[PDB]
Image (cartoon, rainbow, N blue to C red; front, side, top):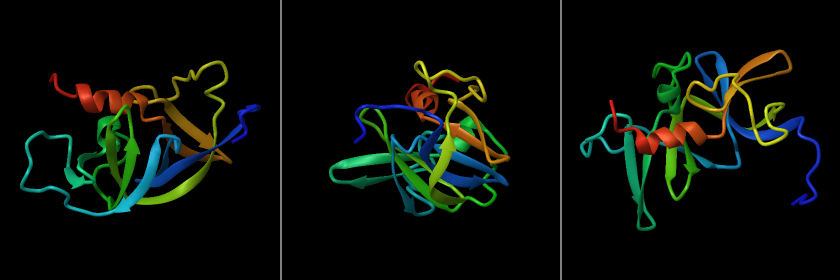
Length: 151
């Protein structure tokens, strides 16, 4: 651990492909990517949560942030799944092909995180090396995961 902390130009993150455009989640919260499909089909009940799974005496809910957010995504090339711990919530997001480690630059954060690049349902839009990508620290997306109920 650096501890001293300094500079905030580049940043490591979790990333996957999303209908031609790239997408990344603050690898800090993101635990690891898991390969699976058609999770918890009969136990349906809600709507957002596509599935769930029991493990280590704790069930985790898998949803599609790309759905909560929107993006080009539309369950077209979806295949891989992602896990993320959030305020005692082991959340999950299914994607197409997750590249994993990503060299995302984050000019957003500096004083205490601030950017409306795509703060419609997350932190915001990301861009690097003349390439388009979506980025989020699962903060607003998770917040909605819990308070989803409302209509």
